[PDB]
Image (cartoon, rainbow, N blue to C red):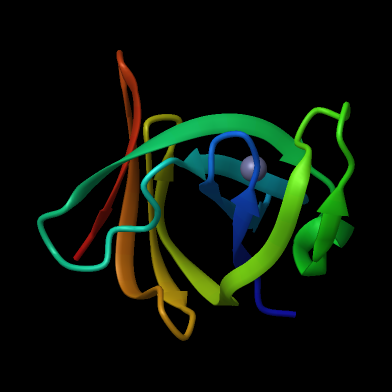
Length: 118
Ligand SMILES: [Zn+2]
């Protein structure tokens, strides 16, 4: 297998959360400066970032200083997910995490991305 996701909490110069989905055989990734929306209605900024390799999904530890992405990475949540809709501008999925669960949607507009919870 079932596709999985991870939300990493990243203590970098700006403390943020990275949402990564196993998708297109890579980790499709977004930085969430204010984290995952925890209830319906909440609209959180999602910043599209570079694909990561699948093996990074279980990573925890310190990215060293002077490297792009420096800081401590921990797993904030993780689980399988079921993809429900996908186009170049919308990704809707059922998350099976311990914190992030139920349906969520990533949307792309001319100003970037947003993450919302059903
Ligand atoms: Zn990060």
